[PDB]
Amino acid sequence: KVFGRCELAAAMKRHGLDNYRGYSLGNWVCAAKFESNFNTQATNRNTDGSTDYGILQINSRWWCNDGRTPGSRNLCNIPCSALLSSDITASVNCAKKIVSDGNGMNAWVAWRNRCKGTDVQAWIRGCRL
Ligand SMILES: [Cl-]
Ligand SMILES: [Cl-]
Ligand SMILES: [Cl-]
Ligand SMILES: [Cl-]
Ligand SMILES: [Cl-]
Ligand SMILES: [Cl-]
Ligand SMILES: [Cl-]
Ligand SMILES: [Cl-]
Ligand code: NA
Image (cartoon, rainbow, N blue to C red):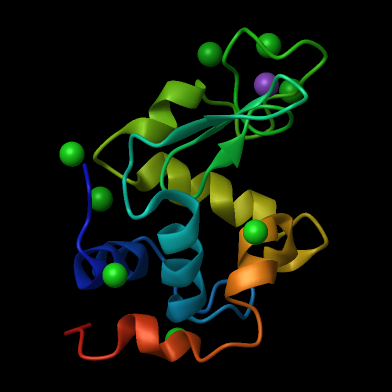
């Protein structure tokens, strides 16, 4: 599924991601924009052989099982395919773990490089929330 901007903001808020660990909703929408362009089915293969999955491009090195990332963990206790669903529950619940791991949203390099320090409220501007 390719979410609309405000549609995704609303779904993230319903799943409790707004201000989670102090990160306002616009931070999460901005991250999803640059990770996946709001496409739940996005996948991308990393140089180390791991793969990133879903709207927040969650990595199989640590967070989900795909059966093809040697030496990896599955700390969200999910198949990586669950991160591609039109229902964002699994991605949100796993993102909550990731953002709590110590480095906050810097875990998403694209958030650090493209969202951090910017006017992230623009990503939710105009949305009925
Ligand atoms: Cl689509
Ligand atoms: Cl957009
Ligand atoms: Cl915001
Ligand atoms: Cl594996
Ligand atoms: Cl594990
Ligand atoms: Cl699995
Ligand atoms: Cl949803
Ligand atoms: Cl980047
Ligand atoms: Na894994």
